[PDB]
Length: 261
Length: 262
Ligand SMILES: Cc1cc2nc3c(=O)[nH]c(=O)nc-3n(C[C@H](O)[C@H](O)[C@H](O)COP(=O)(O)OP(=O)(O)OC[C@H]3O[C@@H](n4cnc5c(N)ncnc54)[C@H](O)[C@@H]3O)c2cc1C
Ligand SMILES: Cc1cc2nc3c(=O)[nH]c(=O)nc-3n(C[C@H](O)[C@H](O)[C@H](O)COP(=O)(O)OP(=O)(O)OC[C@H]3O[C@@H](n4cnc5c(N)ncnc54)[C@H](O)[C@@H]3O)c2cc1C
Ligand SMILES: Nc1ncnc2c1ncn2[C@@H]1O[C@H](COP(=O)(O)O)[C@@H](O)[C@H]1OP(=O)(O)O
Ligand SMILES: Nc1ncnc2c1ncn2[C@@H]1O[C@H](COP(=O)(O)O)[C@@H](O)[C@H]1OP(=O)(O)O
Ligand code: NA
Image 1 (tube, chains in turn brown, green):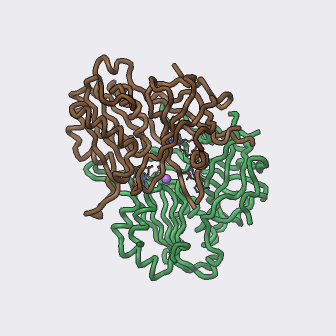
Image 2: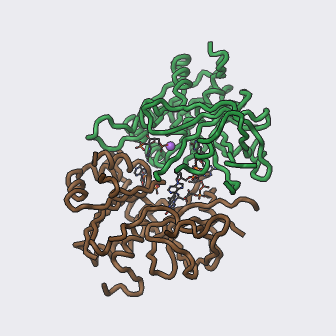
Image 3: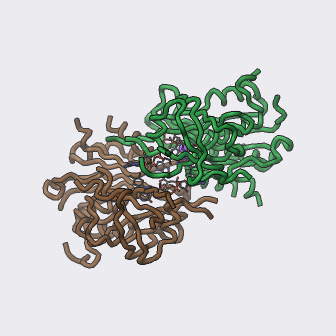
C-alpha cells in the first residue's frame, strides 16, 4: 500500500529535527532516537521500517533498515538506532549516525515490511502480545502511539483491548522508550502489562535467561492469552525467539507476525 | 601488510571453483562453502576477512564481510556463507550466493580485520582458547590449517605442539560447520586439541537457555587455569553475548584477548 515509494534510485531528502540518547549511564549500549522532518512526503503504516542511506551526497550507496517508532498522525517520524562498536571503530551506518548533527540531511527509502497492525484494530478492540528485544521495541511503540492516541504535547487527555508486552534488554537503563512505556503503564493499567526480562544478573550467577524462557516459565497463562483472548502475536528482535515461542504453540497461523534481525 | 589491497573502486575478479553445502540434513540453517580461485593475487593472513560485492559488473556496490577459512599456503581461498531468509525472500548477498554457479565471477575486496594469530605462533607453541558460534568457527578453521599444516591431498608434518581448547555453539550436531576438518584434528592430534560443542537444541522442552557462555561458567576454574597458567591467547567470534560473561570470569592481559563479533 505504501511500499517502495522511495528506493535507492530515488531517496527522499529529509531533515534531522532532534537526536536523543535513548539510554542512561548504566547501559553498556549507545542508541539514538532521531526526530526526522520529511514534509509529509514519507508514507508508512505503523510497524513499517524505513531505509537510511549513509553519506548520500563515492559510488557506495548502501541502505540499512530501521523500524519507525512514531505514529502516522505525527508530523515528523521517529527512529531508534543502536551504534555498533568494535576495536574505537564503528559500523558503517552506525558511524554516520554517530556524527549526525542537528539539521543535517538524511536520505530515506520508502515504506518497507509487513509487520503491521490489522485494519480492524481500534474497532474490534483486538488483544495483543508483543515480544521484543533491544531495538525491537520500536514497532511496538509505534503501535501504542496509534492505539492510545499518543501526543507528547497533549498528555493529560484521552481503544479498550488488553496488551501484554514481553521486553528483553540488559538492565533498567537499557529500556528504550522508557518514558513512553511508563506513561502507558501509568495511564492504562487495566489495558497494558509489561514483563521486563533483564539479561544482567546480581544475587545469582545462574544460566542464560532471556525473553523466551520467561514466556516458557509461565507457558500456560501465555497460551491462555493467545487462545481465550484471541491475541495477535508479534515477534521483533533476535531470531532465537522465533522457534522457542512457536513450539510452545505447537489456520491460526495468520495471527502470528515475525520480524527478526 | 595485506590490509585494503583491494577496495570497491578496484575489486579483484575471482572465480568460483566449488560450492559445497556445509550442513547435514537435521539443520534448520543453510550454509555454503565456497572454494574461490583468486589467481594467487589475494594476499591475507589467517583470521582475515574478505569482502564480497554482490552482483558486480541489483544496482548497489556494497560489500559484506566473510571470514577466510583457509591458510595462506593453499592455492584457492575458501569461505563459509550462511544463507539468510525471512518469510514472504533472501538477504542481499544471501540471494547472490544462493544463485551462484560454478565458474561464476565473484569480486573480492582486500584483507580486512585484525583477528589474527600472533607472528610467534608455531615457533613459540602458544596455547589457545577459541570461542565460536555458527560461522564464527571459520577463522579458527584457517588457524588450525596453518598450525597443523593441513593438506587435503596429504592427510596421512606438524611442528606445533601447544594446546588448543575450542568452545563451539551451534543448533545441533548437523549444524557444526567444518565437521570434517574438526573431527580430523581430534583424530590426528588428540593431545594438542580439545573441542566442547554446546548445542542450543534442548532435546527436552523443560529447560532454559544454555549457550556457549554458560559452559564456560560451568567450567569456571578450568577456563581460568587455561588462561592464567598456560598463557592462552583468547579469541571470541560470533554472538555479542559471549564477550561479557567471559570477561566477567576473567575480571595488561588485554592484548591476549581478541574480539570479532557480528
Ligand atoms: C527489518 C529490520 C529492522 C531493523 N530495525 C532496526 C532498528 O529499529 N534499530 C536498529 O538499531 N537496528 C535495526 N535493524 C538493523 C540495522 O540495519 C543495523 O543498524 C545494521 O545492520 C547495522 O548497520 P551498520 O552499518 O552500523 O553495521 P555494519 O557496518 O553493516 O556491520 C554489521 C555489524 O558488524 C560489525 N562490524 C562491521 N565491520 C566490522 C569489522 N571490520 N570488524 C569487526 N566487526 C565489524 C558492526 O559492529 C556491526 O555490528 C533492523 C534490521 C532489519 C533487517
Ligand atoms: C567481521 C565480520 C565477519 C563476518 N563473517 C561471516 C561469515 O564468515 N559467514 C557468514 O555467513 N556471515 C558473516 N558475517 C555477516 C555477513 O556480513 C552477513 O552475510 C550479512 O551481515 C548479512 O547480509 P546479507 O547481504 O546476506 O543480507 P542483508 O539484507 O544485507 O542483511 C540484513 C539481515 O536482515 C534480514 N533482512 C533483510 N531485509 C529484510 C527485510 N526487508 N525485512 C525483514 N528482514 C530483512 C536478512 O534476513 C538478513 O539477515 C560477518 C560479518 C562481519 C562484520
Ligand atoms: N539469543 C537470544 N535470544 C534472546 N535474547 C537475546 C539473545 N542474545 C542476546 N539477547 C538479549 O537481547 C537484548 C538486546 O539485544 P542486543 O544485545 O542485540 O541489543 C540483550 O539483553 C541481550 O542479552 P545479552 O546481555 O546476553 O546480550
Ligand atoms: N546470545 C547468544 N549467545 C550465545 N549464543 C547464541 C546467542 N543467541 C543464539 N546463540 C546460538 O548460536 C548458535 C548459532 O547462531 P546463529 O544461528 O545465530 O549464527 C545457535 O545455536 C544459537 O542458538 P539459538 O538456536 O537459540 O538461536
Ligand atoms: Na553466530
